[PDB]
Image (cartoon, rainbow, N blue to C red; front, side, top):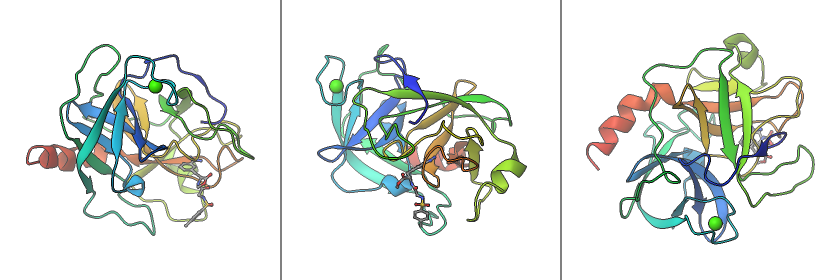
Length: 223
Ligand SMILES: COC(=O)[C@H](Cc1cccc(C(=N)N)c1)NC(=O)CNS(=O)(=O)c1ccc(C)cc1
Ligand SMILES: [Ca+2]
C-alpha cells in the first residue's frame, strides 16, 4: 500500500497473509474455513496466516493453517485478468475471536464515490521498493465507471472496478494482491491489478466480488 497508514494490530481481523515460506499475497477470511483471494495468487503449498500484524514476528494472536484445497474461478483468464478470484479452504477451522474475524459477502454492488478500506503488506513506494512488516491501510473511493473505463490502455470488464485517486500517490501495490477492499462493511473487492502503483491517471483495478457471491456460496456448500 502506497500513501496509506499503519492499520494497528488486528484492526482488520479478516485480513490474511498467504505464505509459501514468505508472504506473497493477501486474502480475506469469509468464514471459519474459507479464504477469498485472487486467482493470480494461485500457487501450491499455501499456508494461510490469520491474526497477523507484524508478519516477521510472532506476536501472540496468529493462527497458521495449511490450505487443504484451492479453487480458482472456472473462467479465470490470466491474459485479461477477468474473473480474478480464488477460494482457499483451510485444513481445519479457524478459531474466531476479536482479532480473527470473518468479513461478510455483499448482497449488492457498492456505489461510485463510496469510501472503501484496502489493506495489505505490499510495497509502500510508487518508485523503488520497501516492504512493511506491519499491516498497511488505505481509504479510497470507488471511481465512476467512465473514469475507470478510460483508466487503462488494456480492456476493463464488468467484473472489475476502480478504487483510488487519479491524481496519484495512493494505491495498492505489489504484495497486496488477493487482499480485501471493504465498503459498507462488506467485502466488495479483491486487489487484482494495476499499471505500477500510485501513478497519475493509473488507479487500482479490483475484482468485483458482488458478481461472484452465487459461485462462492455454491462452491463452499459442496466442498
Ligand atoms: C508486478 O509489479 C507491480 O508493481 C504491480 C503490482 C500490483 C498488483 C496489484 C495491484 C496494483 C495496483 N497498483 N493497484 C499493483 N503490477 C504491475 O505493475 C503490472 N503492470 S504492468 O504494466 O507492469 C503489466 C501490464 C500487463 C502485463 C501482462 C504485465 C505487467
Ligand atoms: Ca506475526
